[PDB]
Amino acid sequence: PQLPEVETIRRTLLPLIVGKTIEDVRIFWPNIIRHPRDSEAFAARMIGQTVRGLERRGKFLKFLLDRDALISHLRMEGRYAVASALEPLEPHTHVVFCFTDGSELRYRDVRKFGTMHVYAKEEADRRPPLAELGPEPLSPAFSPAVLAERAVKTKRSVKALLLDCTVVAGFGNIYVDESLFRAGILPGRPAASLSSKEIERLHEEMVATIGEAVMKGGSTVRTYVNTQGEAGTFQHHLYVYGRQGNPCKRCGTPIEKTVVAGRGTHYCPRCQR
DNA sequence: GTAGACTCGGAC
DNA sequence: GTCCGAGTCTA
Ligand SMILES: [Zn+2]
């Protein structure tokens, strides 16, 4: 899940937990808890607090409690669900927050890559991982000017640049390949090789791509759904991601797949320069 | 500052 | 064996 996915999860999860008081916190896979490092302390400090709100920062969910903030990252396959405490638990449930009303917030993650950090509300923003996060793509803090700034200070590919959460928040593998194709730029291009026109173009497309995505509930390509288990629909609007060997939707040239910045990369050798 | 290797487990 | 909507730790 990237910005669009997490944003949908956020909007649909809030009403299901807002105003509930944590009665217990059960942990079946301690490694997910990053801070405090001792899982017993993590659990003990949550008890008695009420869920006041749910915010997003890049791909992170920020649960606002009374004095604390629970920072959660789903990474590759983490997922939330609110259900009854009387029902058996589905497989791969690693952390459960029990509310005083008998319902509970369950966190599932087949790969166990997800993380959880709990800090006093005022410390959350000045501590990792929210600490070195770049600006929100959909906000003025993210402008062509800002992007140009980081591009020159490096020889690495533009794809590696965009995947860097310190440059811009929330862009992942799918939307990077998709924005580069829309901007007509090869992902392997050195970040510096880009020009002023190419930079403002990329910015334009990043904002539109990410934008259309949230408005469609995200991209379900394998295991993503909102807290209601509903599937997004932006994956029907994908130009390159996951379409290797298939004709480009614009020019008909077969989409190619390579490894760039250590990850699967899709692009149209004809339309992207 | 930056290329790699985990952290893990189920679907082809 | 290969593939994977992520991002911190290495060397
Ligand atoms: Zn094309």
Image (cartoon, coloured by chain):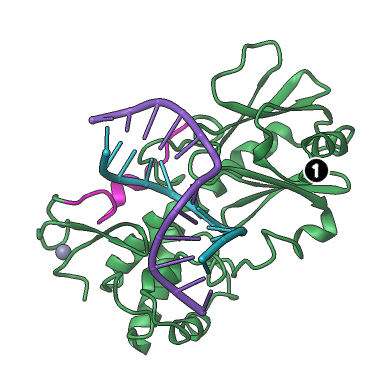
Chain colours: A green, B purple, C cyan
Give the tally of numbered discs: 1
Q: Amino acid at mark 1?
A: Arg
Q: Quadrant of ligand 1?
A: bottom left
What residue appears at the point 56 percent right and 49 percent down from the top-left corner?
Answer: A7
Estimate the x, y position of residue A118 in percent, counting from the top left: 77, 47
Quarter location, residue A260: bottom left
- Of residue C7 and residue A106, the one placed in the foreground of this image is C7
Q: Chain of mark 1?
A: A
Q: Is residue A15 magenta?
A: no
Quarter location, residue A84: top right
- Of residue A146 and residue A41, the one placed in the foreground of this image is A41
Estimate the x, y position of residue A142 in percent, counting from the top left: 55, 75
What residue appears at the point 43 percent right and 53 percent down from the top-left corner?
Answer: A213
Above or below for A93 versus A150: above
Above or below for A208 versus A42: below
What residue appears at the point 45 percent right and 38 percent down from the top-left corner?
Answer: A224
Above or below for A190 versus A212: below
Under tag 1, what secondary structure?
Answer: loop
Majority secondary structure in the magenta region: loop
Residue A104 can be seen in this image: yes
| Relative side of A23 to A192, left or right | right
Quarter of the picture containing the C terminus of chain A is bottom left
- Under 8 Å from ligand 1: the CB of mark 1? no
Residue matched to label 1: A52
| Relative side of A195 to A11, left or right | left
What residue appears at the point 58 percent right and 75 percent down from the top-left corner?
Answer: A140
Q: Residues within 10 Å of mark 1 (few under 14, many from 20)?
A: some
Q: Is residue A234 magenta?
A: yes
Highlighted range, magenta: A230-244
| Relative side of A20 to A204, left or right | right
Estimate the x, y position of residue A159 in percent, counting from the top left: 37, 68
